[PDB]
Structures are given as structure tokens and as C-alpha cells.
Amino acid sequence: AAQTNAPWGLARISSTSPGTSTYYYDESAGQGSCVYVIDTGIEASHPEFEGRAQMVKTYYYSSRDGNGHGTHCAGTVGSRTYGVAKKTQLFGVKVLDDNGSGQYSTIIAGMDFVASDKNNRNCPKGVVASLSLGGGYSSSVNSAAARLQSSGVMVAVAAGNNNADARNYSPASEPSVCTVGASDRYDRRSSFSNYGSVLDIFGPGTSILSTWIGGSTRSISGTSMATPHVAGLAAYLMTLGKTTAASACRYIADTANKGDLSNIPFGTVNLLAYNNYQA
Image (cartoon, rainbow, N blue to C red; front, side, top):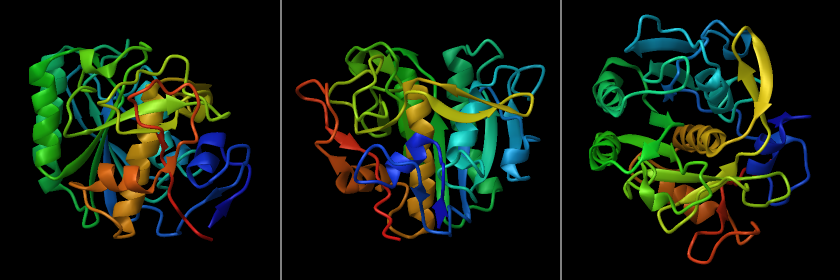
């Protein structure tokens, strides 16, 4: 399949080269997989989601996304125009309030929610969790992310936007999950992107156009938005049978575009998520 005039990030993940605008992907498109977006919620009613998005859990007075960040990430995972995996199922877990903040314990509870809730869902191709969130180092948040990974969910987490080593942030520093940095459309490390040996992969993170609340769209930047690209890619690759939740992060790194990013500090991987689709 070919999506002309796609957002640059979708076009990048199906390209050996920057500077193209068509997204190429197998039509299976993540059908029969599921991605949990653990964030501020999802505006499930957004026409971009086509009935494939639903809120399954909230820790606040409302399950709606009053922020837009979770809606934006869900749109990059699986919205019809802005999504990597245009047919996956999206499950919203609102661990962040509408200011975008959450107590870690609510975040931990939400991760443990996903690790059980996936047994209440039909995801025969497998389960992904996109965690576009983070804060300071926490061994209890790291371990919640490792449990989620261990339960059979590919976990993809933001490296963080501090331009520092990700070892001082959680769940970024958890080694068992898939820690994602951010690149820009010129194949540069995003100026805000964390780095370090704990990063597994980079995805498009600068000026990412996706769904927003109120039925709108907008372009925003963050290792937060690189993560749903990898999360959407994992769901896509799992539907194609190319990998499993336990080995997806590593499959993605094996098959990534290698050595193409600039301003990648010594010791951090120079790998850019790539779907390797041959049209």
C-alpha cells in the first residue's frame, strides 16, 4: 500500500532515505494486533480512528483525553492518516491527568492493568504498549515496565526530552523494554532527545503531525512522539508474523536503518526504525 503526502515520519519509517513523502506498508496494517496507549487517554470519537479506538481504563474523574497528548500518540500508532498501523486496535489507559502529569503509582497501576487487561481483549497477533511518559529514575516504575514486558507485551517507552543520558529516567532506563529516541526529518537526533546505552532505537520525533482533541490535528515534538512510531511499527511487524512481543524491540533494531543519524553521541545506537517494506 502507498499513502501519498503522508507525514514525514511515516514516510521515513518506510524509507532507506530521508526527504520522501509517501508511506509504504503491507496492507495487513496491524490488523488483529492491539496497542495500549498509556497516557492522557484517547479521543476515541475522532474520525481518524474509525471506531478502532476505545478507552478501557482511567484513574481520574473522566476517561476522556482533555490534554491531547495521548490522542496525538494514539493517532501516530493507528489513525488512518497519521498512524503507522492503520488497522490495529487502540486501547486507552489514562494514567496521566489532563495537565499531562501522573503519580508514578497510578502509572505503575496502569502498567499492571495492561498486563492483565490484555487477557480481556482479542489480540491474536499480539499486544503492544506505547508509554509516551516518564520522569526521574524509579526502580519501581522500571520494574512495572519489565513486568509488563515480561507478561508478553512489547513495551515501547520514550527516552525522555532532557538531552541527557536516559539512564537517569524511568521507565526509559529499564533495559528489558524498548527505549526510543527522537530524530528529525533531516536524520538528525532531535535536539531534545535523550541518548545513552539504554536507547534501543530512534524514531521520528520532531514536528510529528497527528490527531488532536476536538477532532483536530497538530504537529508536536518529543521522544514522546517517536515512541508511538515504534509501537505502531511493532504492532505492524507482529501482524506480519515477523516478530513477537518478546523479541520485537530487538527485531526492530536488527532491521533498522543503520548509521544514518547525525549528532548521535558516542555509545548510543545509530539505528532508525524501518519497516523494511518492499512494495
